[PDB]
Length: 160
Length: 55
Image: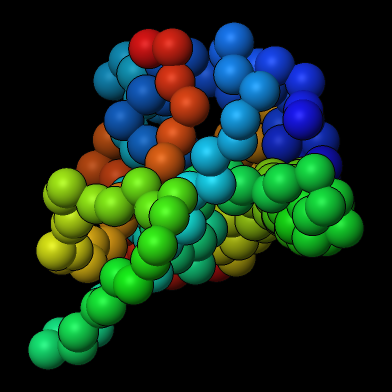
């Protein structure tokens, strides 16, 4: 999208990634499978939980609102009541449909940013001892085990 | 003389007032008073309101 990872440089998401929103695929000699990146998943979940809370908790609950009665010589205060109810409902529907379209795009931008922050983090760890290949995938130069592949996940592997 | 509604040419105008705590009401008349039998000592509520519902 905006940051250019989700449908961008990474072509599609994996259905073998279910444990988190971000993670890694194993392609070592010890076999294939998936291991989730819990730091990018949890910081995305915290941002999503706070925006979900924000959009709900800002909307302070509606108290009892009933229809009001007007006689045949009270059509002005009836049409003033109606103009007040309609004009508030126009503004209310407008603010709700502004917020939903804007913050759904900002959520897509936020998640697309979290794939950048993860990919550039692994590139800065791997450097020369692995090169980019499958636009997301990194071919190890010297080759190494699932322990060394795990060390890249947890924020270590400071090899040039 | 007026148009008959509910088979009645006469009219019947229903009035009201709130009588305050300890206040007296005096009904003085020489004709046409349709006096109370019963009245209603109110208890003010919140969350109440009139709705029109076929449910």
